[PDB]
Image: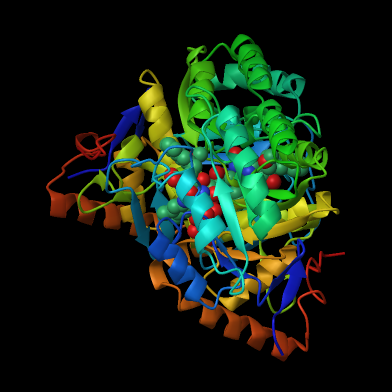
Length: 313
Length: 313
Ligand SMILES: Cc1cc2nc3c(=O)[nH]c(=O)nc-3n(C[C@H](O)[C@H](O)[C@H](O)COP(=O)(O)O)c2cc1C
Ligand SMILES: Cc1cc2nc3c(=O)[nH]c(=O)nc-3n(C[C@H](O)[C@H](O)[C@H](O)COP(=O)(O)O)c2cc1C
Ligand SMILES: COCOc1cc2ccccc2cc1CCc1c(C(=O)O)[nH]c(=O)[nH]c1=O
Ligand SMILES: COCOc1cc2ccccc2cc1CCc1c(C(=O)O)[nH]c(=O)[nH]c1=O
């Protein structure tokens, strides 16, 4: 009985990894995720220049999840490139590097310089499409013409297999359109579903106040609020993108939640809010939990049930 | 202390009502909501002809909420009109009628016939914009040119004050666009935020199966999953539509949840999932709990705190 996977020409002890933005910003964080029993890690989404991000408080969590408007704080691309090229021990586990440029030009600039390190060291690019572009325009992946533009330029500029991080969608015609766009690009070998549920608003009854400072309290939602939405996106893309891998992300607190993601079609399973809250010991719990479920059901490997969610008659 | 209010030229004992679709489809349902402690009721969204709806199972509920793909089962427009015209006791509470035609032409033919009963009896129109139009393309409220057409044609055909039931949005540019469309229509006097969170997927770990039969298990989410999304939509529209009222719908299980919707800006508060699960006794509990939070805070009226959610710095 085993959780091992091999994909994108890499071998993974198990399917768990942090979600981008959680426990991945500093060298300390990245060493910690490397020391964990995660099967991989992803570095904090970066921009060309380092960023302080938004004023605090900018993340808060609660029993059913989290809200954030961090504002892409990060050490800058040069830092994460260096971590990939000189500091990361790939004998431990593979490394994804998330990039989240604020324009298509910024992303092109970073991927041209990532390419030789990716070729040589085997670092895997996760391009964040759930990302602002022009203010007053929708985020990139809710603007299908900008999304096409971004994947065209990055495919050209990078020339290597990469993956994309997607916002949730809530309409079947949007699933149909978004997957068609992704399927235009052979180099997009994996699709991570999902980024947070956009522009939620948490209000504290006692103080009569929003809980985060930026954007009048509006921010992205993660955690238990978003699991069914995350499962639907994973399955929607799994069913529409047969030639690509789908990584699952949203509401994983338990091996049973990871189990559902994998039945929906997930290959890797990312952990954001639950990992922020519980810390990296979560990965041993999740592995034990999923293995216990597999044993009860008589499944010996992930491929025996990946994508095998049943529908009704 | 009593929670009485007046709006749209009608008097309400309190700000609670059922959400459209819940406990509102048959004459029995409607009479049951009328006998409840609710401030108002809305009928099931209707089409010109009666509809059986989608295959069962089509609704399921769980600790954190519900998923449904009911498929607009209803007794048809002639039935709801006759309930509004001959059967409802307006001395008991106001009545809203929800219209959800599958084309713009369907909605115009229904509102033309509704207008004289509205004039004569005071029944209030809630137009459902979270409704498909054409297969292959997005639901109406996610296609702003089609939304504008529906509002233009309906305002012309109906010619009296009405309201709109909106899907959640998740992107600020989309709030800006949707609210500017609605503000083009002086007759749209209320906006109900929000309809269910579209196309989630619930999977049962034991059976490895989705839980509703239609659409391969995909359906709208309500309940606790959706409260911060509903609060964000209530507030976003409240800030953008100073000349309209905003009705809150989504994730109300408690008087505290109703408190948060009103702080966000809600005038009326609709109850779907919680009502489906608890039954119409819920309205007494909600009233008592809201009154209790008001007492503890020293609020004497809803108006003292409606829309008064505090931001940080
Ligand atoms: C504090 C915080 C920071 C995040 N930063 C990023 C980021 O930089 N890039 C990114 O793609 N997603 C980011 N996310 C999104 C998560 O990676 C994830 O998609 C979302 O939280 C849903 O997963 P969850 O339900 O496990 O939290 C962030 C989430 C949180 C809570
Ligand atoms: C079983 C079911 C049937 C529904 N039918 C309708 C409908 O006919 N029209 C409508 O505008 N919304 C309909 N809804 C949406 C609710 O009115 C409401 O917007 C949604 O459930 C979110 O509220 P809640 O969190 O309190 O459930 C329905 C919801 C449920 C659960
Ligand atoms: C459009 O989705 C929100 O994500 C962002 C919001 C930003 C707001 C101001 C400046 C930069 C922003 C960057 C992002 C993308 C980074 C990101 C963040 C974040 O850094 O705020 N939080 C998430 O939940 N997901 C993300 O993908
Ligand atoms: C736009 O998707 C949610 O609403 C509907 C979905 C339907 C699917 C197939 C056929 C008709 C549909 C009609 C609607 C509108 C009625 C409705 C329903 C419903 O009757 O399925 N459920 C909701 O949660 N909200 C609604 O507004």
